[PDB]
Image 1 (spheres, helix red, strand yellow):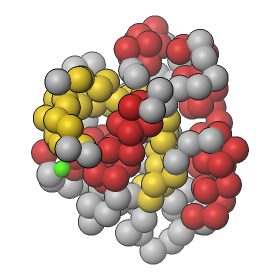
Image 2 (cartoon, rainbow, N blue to C red):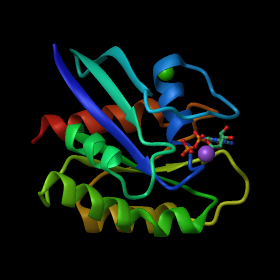
Image 3 (tube, rainbow, N blue to C red):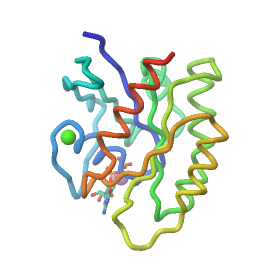
Image 4 (cartoon, rainbow, N blue to C red):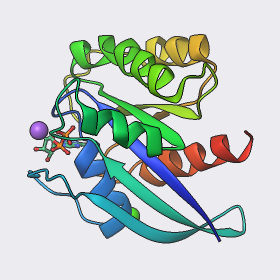
Length: 166
Ligand SMILES: Nc1nc2c(ncn2[C@@H]2O[C@H](COP(=O)(O)OP(=O)(O)O)[C@@H](O)[C@H]2O)c(=O)[nH]1
Ligand SMILES: [Ca+2]
Ligand code: NA
């Protein structure tokens, strides 16, 4: 089968790791201690075609480092995650897109905008705002909760579809 290396980026505490664990292990974690070793592999079927997802979680890597750059050289598609209750994480998204464009040395990198923690009450970012930013990038936007599992499969599977159209 094809193997898809998907890299999850975003500000601290937005839920990169819980999203990854929810996808792979079908559990929601209340806390996650990152390592240098957190890649996760899982076989899934997307649109009738079996494939392998290799999820690389960037949690805990420094904002600018050789390891983070190596991680995104290896990635074929990217999830840019913010949290819908943290406006600053949504404002940081352009920084992660600029970083991916730099490392991949391209303006057309498979990417999906992910608005996580959609179960929480104190929303500060509208779906319309996020859709408008995704639209400016020409990429899909998906709303998720690693806790209720809403949108989790959709976000990773849509990213695979994005790779499959490149
Ligand atoms: N309610 C809620 N909490 C979440 C969600 N995603 C992550 N969290 C919590 O947010 C905190 C940070 O999550 P983590 O995955 O470690 O974020 P990361 O640093 O970006 O990898 C943890 O306490 C998680 O339990 C979500 O969708 N909903
Ligand atoms: Ca799962
Ligand atoms: Na954290």
